[PDB]
Length: 279
Ligand SMILES: Nc1ncnc2c1ncn2[C@@H]1O[C@H](COP(=O)(O)OP(=O)(O)O)[C@@H](O)[C@H]1O
Ligand SMILES: [Mg+2]
Image 1 (cartoon, rainbow, N blue to C red):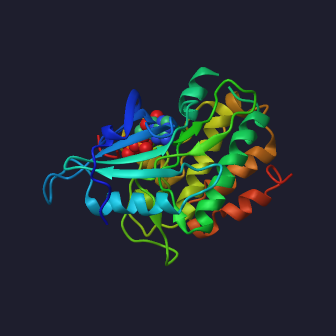
Image 2: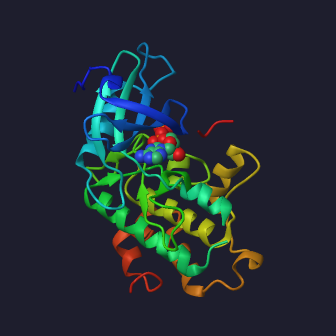
């Protein structure tokens, strides 16, 4: 599909840089016609076939197709798309309160502060999985807060660069994210489905409760090995006054066999809740 090929600067003014990827840079911007603010994500296109730099058109089209389907309080929405010879430019909903990642670097969290965040993440993922969309890159840097300076911040899931529609219950190959957060089936290059997201949620939950990463090794390869082996434990020093139900929630997500892992629907009914790979 093609996108609007007018100069984006004719319609938007750009401001501060909000964030950076290997092939993307995200800048605050303001639409001239409405004065509304957005985040413009500039994704570098492939310059050839078989070039390693930039993102393939097929991959950019998939990210755009998925973003266009989304409208939910806990996910990002897509406003407009532009393109030119070098970039595709996604005008995304602005999330102005920073990464959950940097929020956690400031603040440990109480179990209630952890569940406040987690319930919203689970609601956003329930929405996506209801659509058969696997996000495949869930981690604290890809959660954003609308406002950091409130006692119970609202979050939106961002970064659909690895997301895929799963229309057969699994897809074959193999959308490798960040070693600390990827499920064993990603590590082992096995068919992947919605369950891989649920593993990432267990990793995120462990970190929210402890400030520590459950599988992190000294090298990317050692982390990957730890993940495949399900090499983690609840350190007394971090978890001694965490509730057993919170540990139970994590244990049921950090399960090697995706068939045996909690589903997003299971996770919402759980008693605790129910009311870049190579060095
Ligand atoms: N809608 C948004 N609002 C505010 N900041 C954003 C938004 N989207 C992305 N960012 C920031 O930009 C960074 C990179 O964007 P991302 O979508 O993760 O691109 P990629 O992971 O493909 O490089 C994020 O980690 C975040 O800090
Ligand atoms: Mg990111």
